[PDB]
Length: 161
Length: 49
Length: 196
Image (cartoon, rainbow over all chains, first blue to last red):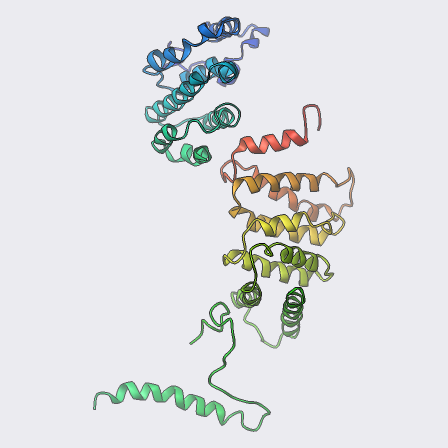
């Protein structure tokens, strides 16, 4: 969309923008927060055979179009709550989603000058490691981590252990 | 002849010790040029001339 | 060996204090003060050059109980400078010193000068610990800060605040001593939701 890629004319803290409960005051943005809410409502009710089409959709459709930081945070806000379901019931897809997260982080670190939100991204990745993946993602992550810019590498250095 | 100049510098320091050991002859001291104590490579006493 | 440790430590404190006690130009103040500290560090290095790995920590508990048993703050700061150069030169693993410093039960908040000098030294030597050790140190420092009352005296507050700079240094995001997720996990394990 123009609201995630080109115009951050409303560039309000995206962790407000993707909070749907903003609908309390009449400040819901658009399909951004609305499709985030409906996607969570649909995937919350989905069987695991229906959720398991998410990794293909990430690594085949979303990964060639995530270019800026708002799209990366939107994909994190979109998929991140269901790693509990994947880690409980089907563990291939949690690993594939972890690799897809690091790949999108690589594309946004390359195709952008600087990140304003490197700290929530880094804390999300540490939370995903220490809660869900652990150390199944070792060899394939370090190629991605070594290609990042210095500040992100400085905060992400503890991933490799 | 040209090896007199390495010697003269060696004869400075020797003479210096003479001028110290004549100095402290009336006070109650014991002078020495070598002190065999341990440490010697960590203490600044190792890092002296 | 315990007696040997006692002898070396006693003689170092007494000697360095007394020769410096009379200021007959004995010293040149700038980095020669650093050299007298090097002198205590070398005396500590000789003492350490004689010990096994498994015996590496009970001697350190003896060192810290001997430092905390002192009363003169100049004596305490001189032995803390000795411990600082003993860590800095690479002789001592910089996790055992910090743990035995904080978990020493003589470290109470009423010993305010001991509190200040101890947490000053831990601020000096915490930068080399690995991150899991930094996490356990964060936990024990928070539990040490938790024993202070709601009200303390108005003079002891600045010397009490020396632990706050260690806490601010650990939870600083640019220094990156540990992953910040570990820091908020230890904090929220100690201050759960609803607790100030």
